[PDB]
Length: 206
Ligand code: NI
Image (cartoon, rainbow, N blue to C red; front, side):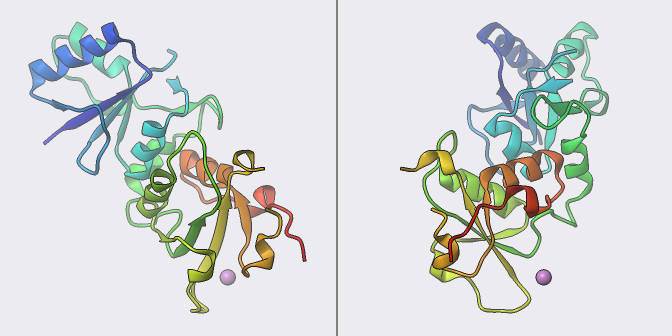
């Protein structure tokens, strides 16, 4: 059926989403899972901030809708079309990138289709497993150890790092993979278009 989480709301706002869920028989949870069908984002009059629920929502090719879907569907005393409320973008990667949509329609051709990714080093605003979960949803295959990369010529390995979380340009010294920054993933995921690694490469010492 339907299952929702919310992002960037206030309790009153949440109250409304509840009221909405209550009336329409929609399941409403604190945590996002595979089952979650909808992510309701606080937006301007339809840009939201980039939250984790925001990313995993796109990663799952789910319904990433602005809070206005809710308040209107209450105002109209009926449930409107997820289609005319969607999140057209966000502050970070442009107010007009249509990420979520792209994501819904692209469930065959996933941006990280046929990749091997190792989220290496420590991470901040994201549990690594969540970052990892993210990339699995985008058709990447997760590696956990630099040295566990597959030898098949067909596959492409990538080391993802978040430089902030350290006290690491020697990666290229420990394997033969490109090193990029978490922004690569994030940026790729919002836009749902696998980015030119170029911008994101980290210097690897010989
Ligand atoms: Ni190649």
